[PDB]
Length: 151
Length: 151
Ligand SMILES: [Co+2]
Ligand SMILES: [Co+2]
Ligand SMILES: [Cu+2]
Ligand SMILES: [Cu+2]
Image 1: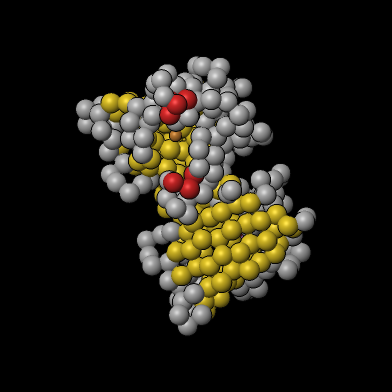
Image 2: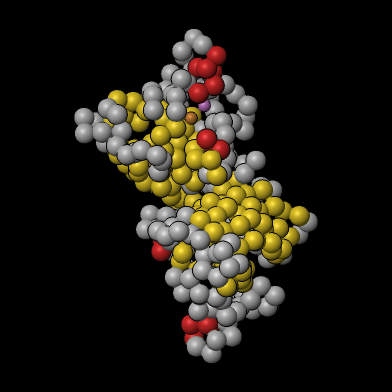
């Protein structure tokens, strides 16, 4: 499993396609998201690839190491913690992320899991509430999609 | 992964939810599909979990052993060859299968791949034409979805 793809869709105007490519011991995440309100939005990998109930069924962030919510560069982060994507004035966000924690194979494999883009920005668990240590206070799930094997 | 799910959707009335469960050394496929034309419909695992171009981007049938298209009971078949589902008068198909070739882990894993329900009945590789040895003349893909890890 060296390439994956995800199509983000939801109940609103938010849409996008994310590409995953394994490079060395990292995964390179690229793509774009549209129909986003300007600014930052939490971008995470949720535990389940279950769409039965929309984005709600994806569960919490992928967290095999049973840690607290954090930023991508933090040591105490969920594996699904990719931090933030930033939409321009016209509501477009270009995704360009490199991450050593997520993987396309084995234990930390994200294939068959769900990618979610949130309503508010991710505080990286520095909010001071409890919530910050769980969710980053990213709010609602604007769009999501199952990560699948790509050519 | 021992439990998986798939939510089928398309540009039609057809939809459904199919579940996969690892029971013993085999995989049990259950669920239901609606909005189908009465009769048989090809039901296969396509290779790519790429939904960027609808079900089209799912590629051909999952076929790691490089065999020709066949029926679920044939020696010569694609791993993705689950045969046909049958729709009742009221256009409802109930899925209930056990398969010795598909898996939820390892080289035969269908996780991250695409379940597709076709417009026509599957030939089971017995049509007499090339197309038979490929898709069973199952025709267009009415609905599909990427198989994700479930709770
Ligand atoms: Co998190
Ligand atoms: Co086939
Ligand atoms: Cu999240
Ligand atoms: Cu097919």
